[PDB]
Amino acid sequence: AYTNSFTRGVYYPDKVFRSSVLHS
Amino acid sequence: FQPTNVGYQPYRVVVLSFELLHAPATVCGPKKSTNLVKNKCVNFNFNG
């Protein structure tokens, strides 16, 4: 069987704090 | 490996890999820590 993931599965890519920023 | 073997001889090797990360340090050098100073211009060192 199947379902859609939607926007799940994003994770913090590194152990650095950042705020108010659009990182890539 | 006979003792009569020069590059034919056995060599022991150790490779040290450093888990260098922007994360909690836990193996560090013998360098001592100071007290902490705030609201003044200072030449700091945190975990290297």
Image (cartoon, coloured by chain):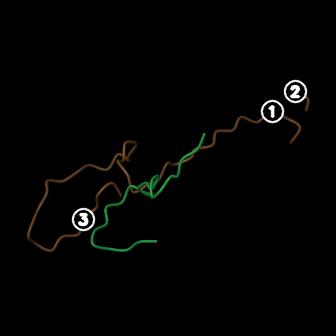
Chain colours: A green, B brown
Q: How far across and how far down the image is residue A20, in percent?
A: 27, 72
| Front: mark 3 or 1 | 3
| Chain at numbered mark 3 | B
Residue under circle 1? B10
Q: In which quadrant of the rendered image does the C terminus of chain B lie? A: bottom left
Amino acid bearing label 2: Phe
Mark 1 or mark 2, earlier in chain: 2
Q: Could you tell me which residue is drawn at 10 percent across and 72 percent down?
A: B40
Distance, label 3 to label 2, CA atoms, is: 52 Å
Q: Identify the element where label 2 is drawn.
A: loop
Q: Secondary structure at mark 3?
A: loop
Residue highlighted by disc 3: B44
Residue type at mark 1: give it: Pro
Towards the viewer: B4 or B20? B20
Q: Mark 1 touching mark 2, by CB under 8 A?
A: yes
Mark 3 and mark 2 lie on one chain; the one further toward the N terminus is: 2
In three-dimensional space, the C-alpha distance between marks 3 and 1, rounded to whole angstroms, equals: 46 Å
Report the chain holding disc 2.
B
Q: Amino acid at mark 3?
A: Phe
- B14 on left or right of B43: right
The residue identified by callout 2 is B1
Q: Nearer the viewer, residue A7 or B13?
A: A7
